[PDB]
Length: 210
Ligand SMILES: O=P(O)(O)O[C@H]1[C@H](OP(=O)(O)O)[C@@H](OP(=O)(O)O)[C@H](OP(=O)(O)O)[C@@H](OP(=O)(O)O)[C@H]1OP(=O)(O)O
Ligand code: NA
Image 1 (cartoon, rainbow, N blue to C red):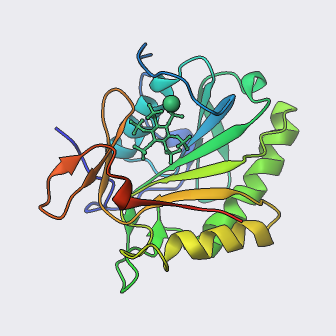
Image 2: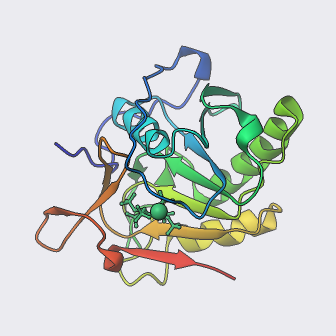
Image 3: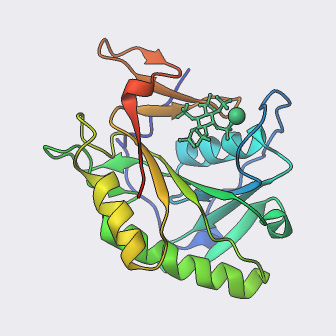
C-alpha cells in the first residue's frame, strides 16, 4: 500500500540524533541513472518519510548517500559513503508537503521555500567541510506532495529554485503538483484526477531549469 508524502500527522524535524534509522534494502532492477551519485536528504523524523528515503537509496544502492538533517542544521549519514559523491549529482529531498494554498503546498518538512534553500546551502558547506567532498548538486528532485501549482507555473518549486540560486546553488528542480508516494523499489507514484496511484504520469511533474 502506498503512503502519501502529503502530511496528516505532527511534524518532528528536531534533534537528528533522536531520529529513527531504517534499513536500506538494495533493489537490483533500478536501471541506469544520469547521476553519478546522489544524496537522499531526509527532512523529518516520520516513518513514511524515512522509508521513502531508504527506498530511493535502495534503487541505486552503490551510489546513494542518505542524510538526515534537523531544524538546527545538524546532519548525519545513515547510508552510503560520501566518497562516491563525485560527478553529476542529484539531491532527492524527502519530506511531507503541507500548508495548502491557491498554488498548493507552501512547506516541506516545515520549511518555506526560502528557509529550505538556506538550510541546504548551509548543509552543502557543512557536509563538504566534515566529509571533505564536493556534494554540489546539478538537480534537486523534490520528493514531497503537491509542491508546485496544478498548472506548474507557480508555488513552492518556483520560489525554491530562485531561493536556491540566491543562496549560491544554481540547480534544476523537479517537483510534483499531486500527491506523491515512493514504493518498495524506490519508484515514485502520483495521484491521477480520479485519486488513483499511477506511475510515470509526466503530467503531474515539472522540471524547472535556467
Ligand atoms: O529511469 P527510470 O527508471 O524511469 O527512473 C526515473 C529517473 O530516476 P533514476 O535516476 O532513478 O533513473 C528520473 O530521474 P531524471 O533523470 O529524469 O531526473 C526520476 O525523476 P526525478 O529525478 O525528477 O525524481 C524519475 O522519477 P518520476 O517517477 O518522478 O518520473 C524516475 O522514475 P521512477 O519513479 O520510476 O523511479
Ligand atoms: Na533511469
